[PDB]
Amino acid sequence: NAEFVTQLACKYWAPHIKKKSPFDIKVIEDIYEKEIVKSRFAIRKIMLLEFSQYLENYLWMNYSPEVSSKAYLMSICCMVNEKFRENVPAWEIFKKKPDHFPFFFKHILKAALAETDGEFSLHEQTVLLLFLDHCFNSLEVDLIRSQVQQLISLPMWMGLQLARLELELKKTPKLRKFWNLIKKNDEKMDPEAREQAYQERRFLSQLIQKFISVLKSVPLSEPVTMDKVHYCERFIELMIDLEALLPTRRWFNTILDDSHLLVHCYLSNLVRREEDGHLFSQLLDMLKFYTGFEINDQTGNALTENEMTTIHYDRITSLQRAAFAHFPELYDFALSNVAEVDTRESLVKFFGPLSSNTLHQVASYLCLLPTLPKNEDTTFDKEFLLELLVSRHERRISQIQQLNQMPLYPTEKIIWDENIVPTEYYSGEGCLALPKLNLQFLTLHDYLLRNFNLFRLESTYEIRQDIEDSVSRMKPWQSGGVVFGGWARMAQPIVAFTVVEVAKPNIGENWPTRVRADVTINLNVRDHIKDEWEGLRKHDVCFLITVRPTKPYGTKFDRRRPFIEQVGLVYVRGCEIQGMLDDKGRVIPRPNLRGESRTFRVFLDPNQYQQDMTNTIQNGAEDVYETFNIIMRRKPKENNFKAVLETIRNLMNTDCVVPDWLHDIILGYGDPSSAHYSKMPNQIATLDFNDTFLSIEHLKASFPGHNVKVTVEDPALQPFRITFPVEAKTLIVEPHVIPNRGPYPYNQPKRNTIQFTHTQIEAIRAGMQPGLTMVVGPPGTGKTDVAVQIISNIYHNFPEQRTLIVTHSNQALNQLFEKIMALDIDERHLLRLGHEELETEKDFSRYGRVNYVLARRIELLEEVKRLQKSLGVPGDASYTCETAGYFFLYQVMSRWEEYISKVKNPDVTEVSTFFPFHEYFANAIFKGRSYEEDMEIAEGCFRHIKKIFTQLEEFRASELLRSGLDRSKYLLVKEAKIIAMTCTHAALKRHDLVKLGFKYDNILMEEAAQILEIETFIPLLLQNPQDGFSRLKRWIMIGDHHQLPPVIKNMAFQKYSNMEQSLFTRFVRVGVPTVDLDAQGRARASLCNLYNWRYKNLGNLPHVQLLPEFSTANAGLLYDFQLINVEDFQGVGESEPNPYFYQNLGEAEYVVALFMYMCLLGYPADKISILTTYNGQKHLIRDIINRRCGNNPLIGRPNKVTTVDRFQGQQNDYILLSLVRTRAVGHLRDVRRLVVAMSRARLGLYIFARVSLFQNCFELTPAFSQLTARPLHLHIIPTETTRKNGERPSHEVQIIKNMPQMANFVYNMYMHLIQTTHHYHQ
Amino acid sequence: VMTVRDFTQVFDSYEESMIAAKMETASEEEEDDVDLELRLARFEQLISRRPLLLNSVLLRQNPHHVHEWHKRVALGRPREIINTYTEAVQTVDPFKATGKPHTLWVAFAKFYEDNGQLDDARVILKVNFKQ
RNA sequence: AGGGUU
């Protein structure tokens, strides 16, 4: 009934249909019963409805209390849930018309609590659970928060057992007055508002009771309906999210504990079902982590180890009090030591023998259960009662100890578990046992662990995929031995394997500190492969694999079938290369080894080793480490997972000392603006802006809302210092003079040439101040110029404050260093770290910088020699940095001090007459005009000489350190003032950097919205704390959250967990104030309109507005941009020759034909790049390029043929864009992908798509409403330039109405050009 | 190599420096292992330091090192409980620990003191084995 | 992909 839902849409609510039939309630009723319910909530049906804008155009705007029904409520929730599944804005229509949302919300609550199997089915109530989960996860929306407040505030505690409430009020006496105040205010309520309030206050506690009864209805072994399982799963998901967010946790945690839900769940039949309850069990483990999380519910602070111990001690103590006073049969047990009594074992020993009635009575004295009336039997199971008391009082290991026992490699028990390692096929219909990234985290440990686990799971999934690819290729067959029918590049048969070291555990740990093994392979392979295997280096991670093949020899493998059964997968273990052995038995001027056998010494995960050994010793399990028969290596650039996890673990272990003005914002709570410079207590009043402003006019124009007062009236005297107040809109500007640097005018400093806008100035100003500076920089708004100006200003204002620069890509680093080179920054203070093709004019790597220092030292020591001789000092020996230092103090400073004593303690003539360095500067002095002038000229000469000796003193280290590595260490730890690297490198090298004693004061980042959350956090901690506090003074982040996010290989982790969300993006969402750059300078204003709607006030720079090059039309094309409709070609639109390898022959051929048309017009083929949203189409366009252009002299090649995602930060003059899709919109619905796609062109953008499909997409409307304002048929001018954008053309305009007509035209045009011309490349 | 030892004496003359010194001793530790025992006699930074001392005690078969390690753990109620657990697990001798707990369990007012005393009495109470 | 004195 796809024609049914669509026809309804067209009639009643579809977009781009002028007139619709009026609202009819029966449409909602019919669609819900016959389309949604009857199809068993089929995802494709729900998608069609959602995409057709059912919620925005029919459901909500026609919703009222009078028309509300079951079908109406459910339909709204289905649409909202689907929007979350598709990661599009879910709440906008409610925000537009908020009036009836409170009524709607209250009735969602009623429906959720409705009797099981009653009016609402269990699936329908699962849908409601998920919807409510989205609500609780969306408290940033005022409309939602105002409804949810009453469900989760202190008054919810009226759902507590009366004894537990009193216990809590006694525990926190200050709570009682607030409790009383609530009871008083309740009196002022009318009877219905009171009843509504009480129902809301009891909702979550009552929801728990509903869950518990659903859970209990699950049989142990008999068949169970999946709807019960999924309800229970979604319920625990809700519990986790409520518990992992402080505002929802604050009061609800006590409620959850009072209900004893967790004990119910661990004793349940469902967890005991190994297959059915597996996901439920994993969700349960997550919930347990949070119900016992180490945080104070009221203060929100993390609990110390002492506080934890006290909590545990106090519980035992109160249990012993009750034991002593009221238990005789167990009276002897009470007398037990608290520690002995506390272990699980001791507690079972003491309380296990007791009757159900006695245990119930014990629990009642702890306010855990109601009193058991005299002579009554308890209704609770003994195992419940026992587990209740035991679990509550047993010793717990801390969160840190728990983390420190985790292996860093995935095993075969993890790699194929799709509850925690989902495939890319994950629809989003079920939930996963995964952490979620949104806005807030409980503590730093919570924050770090969520990122740890999310990073861990994706890497494990990738490893599993790699293993499947390489192990399948090896074709493991039975021979009871294994024979490999194939070979693999990335995996080899193991010839020998031996554990060679199991070291003793460190104090406080139960695992070996180090496990090593020797693994031998036989490189009977192609020399290319032999070289790659010998290319393995220290810290490279490999996987050790055990297969016991299931198939006879010759049996075909099917990749579609379950991998584990196919090859007989038994074990997977990770390892880390220490080094390859040489023929002297040494772990590796690398040698040339002989033969084809190679042995590698590797590290095994010590925690995994202990667990396996324990399993072997205790349970007779076979020794895993005697079974490996395959070893697999990976691509180094895709194989950093283990190092990153270790770094995260180290960060968790350390005290994580981040700036106190950052901690709360990082965790996402508290005032998002509290780190803004205007709110920093150490805000600096006066700043030297140096070369930031080109003139006093530029400066005045840079501060629109301020009154500028200059300390000097003469306009000819107007670098600038600016003083900021603390009338209060007044800036005091002081012009000053750069100190003379010597008699060589070329040694005057380089200067900034960029006339920064007032907005760019606000960014630069903020970056110079202490605190958090966030800059949102739309395409081409000058992010890089802002960055280097901030860096330059910090460099000059705060010499020996060191700046750390972190980017995502090496391209951004190339751009920064390029612009840095044009500014007044000494290259000896620059350093670039990396694990690369040199793209800058100078080499800023450790290698390049060591070499510069060495070469500069030589030149400077020669200057000292020349100075020596000019002074008539004898001595033929050359100087070292050491003797140069002696020379400066003894020969130079002495002469200068004597000189200053004469002329600065007074004629113009005596400035020159007594100047001690005439001969040295003969190659270059005094003007004899005034004293002040010549004196400063003399001063500048001394500064020139002093700079020589300052550098030589810095360079002495290269005389004390011979090796290039030690020399590079000196530059990194001491000499450089600006140190740059990628976030990737920073993550890998943090351990080494901290060990070196790396220090820095300021961090600047670019591409910030492209960097993963945890890889943004790590660069904050590349150093040790200073006197107990972070040394970090500034944090500048520059990025664009309206462009593409960090890349997540498996998009299931984005769909469920929002793992792609950068820290930058989270901070913007949290509400951290941003500086939004508002004037782009790389593309036509006309093209800028296609994306500037997305940003705050994004306009254009003057040169874009005024330069001819932006108003000159594109030859042979009427419009500078067009959207071109492309219907079917030979009955096909989009095609899929391989699964998900989306293509569109009609579009591809048209694009190539246009490219050919342009080349035949004389376009620079290199100035054209071709983009598409799918890799399948990319290869197809390339295919057609080679098969149609081929060996054509008149037709070149486009600079690139690639995807939009691979063209981030890149551009060309002309972009040819293919959107490919005809059936569904696909991932272009992500507006960020849209914005990037709309902004890759400087001068020309031509898009080929099924226009109708994308027009219907609500999120894409602001772009496509502009694109469809122009014809959808390509307007060409084939006889054409100096024609301007607006002027009517002096040639014929022909309209190409389709691709075949174009391919015809281009053929005829070319056959006319082959006859009339002849070009000649060979 | 000697210089590190010289530095250790300087550390001995004197928290982070204590960490550097304890790491210097744990770097491996003969008579030095017993000396760590001196560190247990003086101070332990965290259960982990105490755990390392316990490991040294485990490493040396003779009883006194283990007794010292247990004492280090105590220095209150939690430490005493840990010592009691060690005694329960330890079958080596009842004398050293006997007196320890006696004076250690003289800071308790009630029930557990009488009950605790009874438990101690219970713990106290071929050929010899038959007798 | 890393450097030094009886």
Image (cartoon, rainbow, N blue to C red):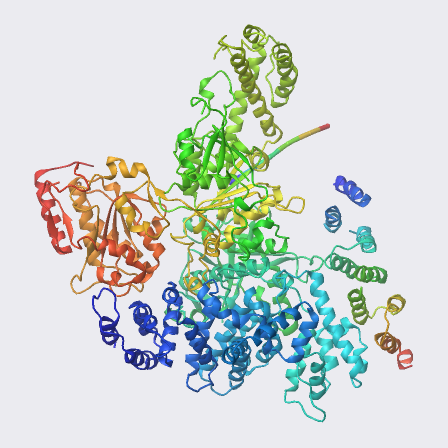
Residue B119 pos. (x, y %): 85, 77
- Whether residue A538 is situated above or below residue A271 in the rendered picture: above
Q: In the visual, does A784 lie left or right of A541?
A: left
Q: Quadrant of the C terminus of chain A?
A: top left
A1099 and A143: which is toward the camera? A143
A1123 or A408, nearer to the observer: A1123
* Residue A26 screen position, x and y as percent: 28, 80
Which residue is more in the foreground, A643 or A952? A952
Q: How many marks?
A: 0
Look at the picture and state if A1155 lies above or below A123.
above
Q: Find residue A308 and report its horizontal and vertical position in percent.
A: 69, 65
Depth order, front residue of A870/A999 = A999
Q: Is residue A419 visible?
A: no
Image quadrant assignment for residue A474: bottom left
Camera sees residue A158: yes
Residue A799 coordinates in the image, percent (x, y) = 56, 32
In this rendering, position of residue B70 left or right of residue A484: right
Quarter of the image containing the N terminus of chain A?
A: bottom left
Image: B25 above or below A1317 = below
Report whether A1277 appears left or right of A195.
Answer: left
Residue drawn 22% across the image and 62% down it: A1252
Residue at screen point 52% across, 86% down: A219
